[PDB]
Image (cartoon, rainbow, N blue to C red):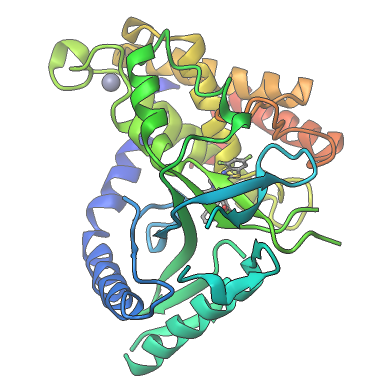
Length: 344
Ligand SMILES: Cc1nn(-c2nc3c(F)cc(F)cc3s2)c(O)c1C(c1ccccc1C(=O)O)c1c(C)nn(-c2nc3c(F)cc(F)cc3s2)c1O
Ligand SMILES: [Zn+2]
């Protein structure tokens, strides 16, 4: 059924051609928002990080990160979670959001939301409150934009990342060092009621960079000889999960699975298969099959290390229970045995 996979990819490309216009609407609203926000003393250095689509099958649902540099940050890991932190300061335009020594995600979300509500009120845009994403904008008839606030730190990545991003045999030890000199991000995100002043690490910019500059060869996919199917494999994996989540929206079994699980699984497969010749475009069928198989193996063993924080198990039974993983395992295996009927 490799041809059927290409059929899917054809459809997905069409949907992207016919959304350029929507992305224009989004850029205009977002540019407006950023100008107003930059006049607030708290948000003076607000900017775009890189739009993106968390759901490949939802072309009108956009996703945008507003970054804000926080100099001289000091992090305090929450409860050995490796991914969630309290934000302190070494020595402040954010001082108004302090709860004691801690930058309050609650308060900084409050103001972020207030200001956005103001500007939307002045513009045919409508808003709705969602911590990350913080708000959802309705633009025109059927365009949504989730906006995440993200603190930026130009300091060294936290200790939990020391053994992560194991790209050395694939993208190289040089690239790994360059990427770890880039900043990292913190999004407001409560941890399990719930600890309500934690911030979670975010490496979405690094994920973006790897996906778009993904070969061992620097010229991978820039000529006929070197076309690979890495990006097509990830698209197919995302579309598979999205179709299944839609199909079983009435069950609780697939609610905790997201595109981040699929994308994490994929990067692990890139690590296991570092040579570009292992991703020949002519081998799309077996390449996707081997991505599907890897994700399934993560499901059955309940092991999916965060690609950047290897001690963080995305498939822990504290996060997703065994029954849910077994259901998804059964459904994917059915799809794969039947040439993926869910695609149509
Ligand atoms: C990737 C993703 N996909 N997805 C869906 N996919 C589907 C789908 F496929 C079908 C469907 F119907 C519905 C959805 S929604 C989603 O919501 C996300 C969220 C996200 C998207 C947009 C705004 C905010 C969030 C957010 O919550 O932060 C997301 C992001 C971008 N990063 N991230 C993590 N990064 C780290 C990390 F760096 C370290 C660590 F230890 C843990 C984590 S977790 C995470 O969880
Ligand atoms: Zn390539």
